[PDB]
Image (cartoon, rainbow, N blue to C red; front, side):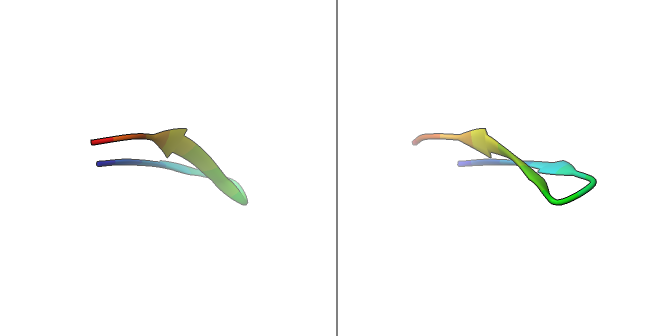
Length: 13
């Protein structure tokens, strides 16, 4: 899980 902004971000889960 994760996400972000401006293009994306990251996460994991």
